[PDB]
Amino acid sequence: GSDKTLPDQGDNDNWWTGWRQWIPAGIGVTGVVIAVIALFAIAKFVF
C-alpha cells in the first residue's frame, strides 16, 4: 500500500507502462500514441 495499491509503480510499473506498452508492435508506442495523437495532431493542424 504505497500508491496505486502496493506496487506503487516502483517494483512493477512496467506491467502496464513498460513491456505492456509495446508487447507486440504498435499497441502503446505506436498503438496508443497513434490513436491519441490522431486527435492532438489535428488540434495543432487545424489550430
Image (cartoon, rainbow, N blue to C red):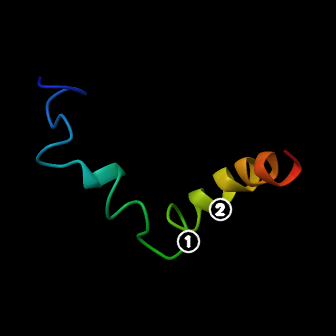
Residue lying at 81% horizontally and 51% vertically, measured from the top left: 42
The quarter holding residue 21 reads bottom left
Where residue 17 appears, x then y in whole percent? Answer: 35, 52
Q: CA distance from mark 1 to mark 2?
A: 8 Å
Of tags 1 and 2, the one toward the viewer is 2
Q: Which mark is residue 5?
A: none
Say which label, 1 or 2, has the lower sequence index. Answer: 1
Amino acid identity at mark 2:
Ile
The quarter holding residue 10 reads top left
Where residue 35 appears, x then y in whole percent? Answer: 68, 56
| Structural crowding at the residue carrying mark 2, measured as other residues with C-alpha within 10 Å and reported as few (<14), some (14–19) or many (≥20) | some
The N terminus lies in which quarter of the figure?
Answer: top left
Determine which residue is flagged by label 1: 26
Q: Is residue 38 left or right of residue 20?
A: right
Amino acid identity at mark 1:
Gly
Q: Is residue 43 left or right of residue 10?
A: right
Q: Which mark is residue 34?
A: 2
The secondary element bearing badge 1 is classed as loop
The secondary element bearing badge 2 is classed as helix
Where residue 33 appears, x then y in whole percent? Answer: 58, 58
Q: Is residue 29 above or below residue 1?
A: below
Q: Nearer the viewer, residue 47 or 27?
A: 47
Q: Is residue 32 left or right of residue 4?
A: right
